[PDB]
Length: 79
DNA sequence: TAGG
Image 1 (cartoon, rainbow, N blue to C red):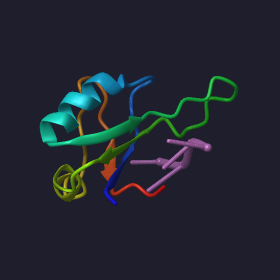
Image 2: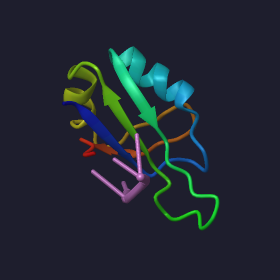
Image 3: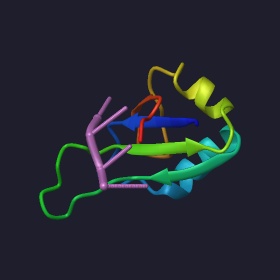
Image 4: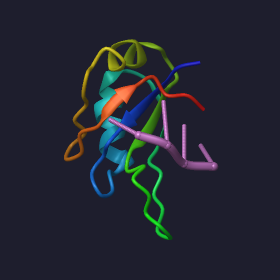
């Protein structure tokens, strides 16, 4: 498996760029930006799985990430 | 920064 846990994202990052940024990274598997309209916790972050393990191999090495407008700390994600 |  290969996932990257992005930490600290804008008020609503569009998986679309995340798809480009990370897509351009390589083969993105999926992008899940969790949002709570009931309490809006401080999770304000996004998860990204790569079909491949390269974007993942590099992502984890990247202290911080910048997606279009959003910029969050990506540490290999865990599901 | 932690979804589901």
